[PDB]
Length: 159
Image (tube, rainbow, N blue to C red; front, side, top):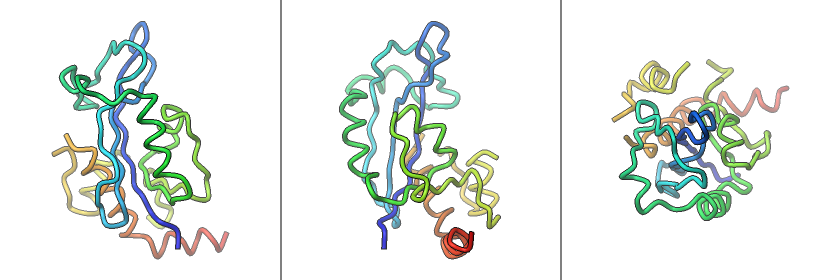
């Protein structure tokens, strides 16, 4: 039995026009939705776009923010050898610069048992996400997996 975790990441726009998505905040949960991680991450570059409409992040959060160098080291130690649940997580792998194995990667962006996580978390759980809590968006991705855990893993072996 492999230990399970779910993750949700918020990015900010660094670079000349905020074109580069830099990790700004992360949250990781168990199979039971307990908190393994939740911290504001100070990107190494200057933050040109906070993308608050999509991040919920402003400057006040970057005060007392765990630098990206530290957080990455912290974050990875959880993920190692754990089955990780995440919505479009390969998009975040590059901003974590860790491209976690595929046989342990479960992307709620495609649940082949059968789109934003907001609509999918109401459309399937009757939970309204977006009520500034990557913790909540992590548990949502986690419960979205437990909702389909049994039908998930069988087809993963049958093919």
